Image (tube, rainbow over all chains, first blue to last red; front, top):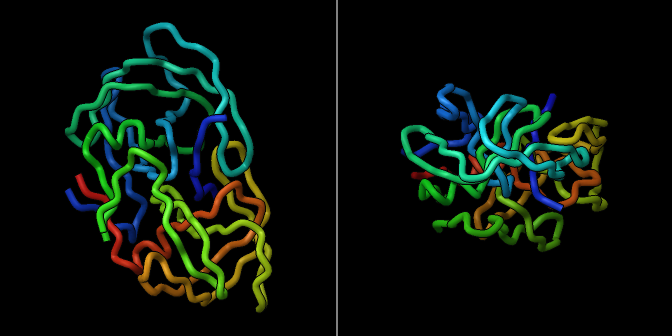
Length: 10
Length: 99
Length: 99
């Protein structure tokens, strides 16, 4: 299950 | 409002005239929404997450209403598993983490 | 304390006798730390996000100190680009989102 939505740009 | 974390911090947002559910995500620099059509010119971009990088479409100066509060900024659209409201817009509505 | 979101919400944590910087991520259900050797039994697990899934090792009942606040719970270990403190541990220190 998708549960960790870390996000950032290059 | 004060939102506890026993459950996912989901809120309703209004964008492009539609209502969508989104996660207040302090772990994302940007705001990423699932595939959808937004007006205006868009440019290709790439963002990274826990399982790699993906291609998205960047839309600038897009008005978004998060749980009532108004924000206007950059919105990325692409194959994200859930709609995410990142720090770029969370700062605009005065959101902070408290404990 | 009150943490603004102008920059990534990084804080110092203590685990297994080590101090590390971890991102307070209301967008993560669990806590995932970058590869580190922790004693004890673990179970294989897959977690996903933007870009896809990664394989991690799950440890239970691990004591962790987040900015002086004591917490104890599950910690996942794997190739994550950054240390992440998720909701499972944030609820323990009474962390809330406010706006």
